[PDB]
Image (cartoon, rainbow over all chains, first blue to last red; front, side, top):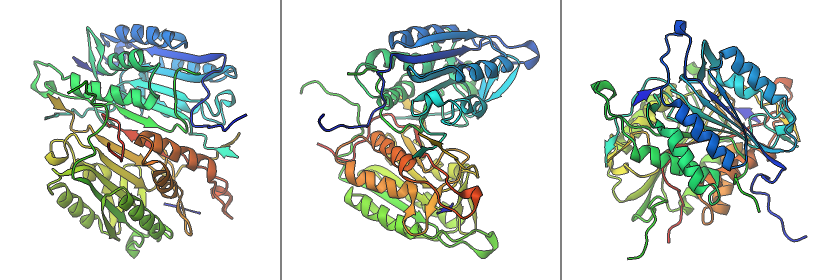
Length: 4
Length: 4
Length: 240
Length: 240
């Protein structure tokens, strides 16, 4: 999980 | 007609 | 029992819920804000419309910014366990992200935060509807001739106008958006899901209204409302 | 003929329309923006999903801000007379109101303005859908355990996340929002109106996803997408  |  | 579906909010609690109408017509002289002629027509139309949907309507008039915040805080601390939903209607001046108390602005985020899923537990999982008749800026539309859940889930913001734009109010008839919203709720609340009602409101505002002004800057202008949905289920005002 | 109703967009033009997918994975080193692992999964899933809806899909990868603006301008100047609708999907970094080209930001308003009712006449009155997988800020959702028309009319912005919030992307599976959107379109596009499909997307994202991180700041977080509708009619991808 990563943020944009 | 009027604006808010 | 037989097969079950979970696609619509449970709207058969003992009570539909509160409908808080904040009607700001007269503003403190020092703010320089004009009086909002026609807004009492809107407030009365909303009171009757939501009464017929079986909401417990509370009308409040000419609240300061401090009174708005206190009212929203207090309402968010009531026990809504027996209520299906919550509705708040804001009728005032505004700018993007802001609605005006009689003596200055209130951040819309401050108002709505009281009802977050983690801060109002008796409304968690229930639809929280904010209906906003206020400007969102000063642009004019010239027209063209033709398990956890998120704390921000289950809100719907029914804005009268597109982001950045003025919102139009007629001093005799009420605001274009509120007039249209009440008419579409009266006609369709026993028939259509709420997003489909609001889409009919969008069409009515977009097609049936155009400004008339002696000032060329403000003449022949158009408006489209803006439905902002964080809802997770279909919403019907009736139940089976 | 018999009685007629006009509540849904005409979707039986010879062509459904274009689906422009802008897939920005790799950013110029000088911007300091990280690569967006998982975005190719999203782009492939969208291409297949919109292909099955009979859209003319054009995939574009790693466009600069200048290339994004030129592409949107050029597409808006095509003749869309025989097309029912227009779809643009943006996969990139972003902030509120902004999506990133590989070398810097583009205002979303600049992109969408090319398609205004007065500036793209062959799309006037037709639905213009912008699907946006990008951050809208840096807030994290902690969750809780359970006749003229307006020039801005007929747009729908299907945002992956609430205003002000980060948007979550899994490096293996793709973004939470795009995964869910494609699944719900595959399951329901022959059955449900578009707002109802997007509401199922809201529920899927809100209930089935939660972040896992070794960093406590980013761990156990939730997301709700945000449907922003200026549409004036119901939208069904099928026709009779």
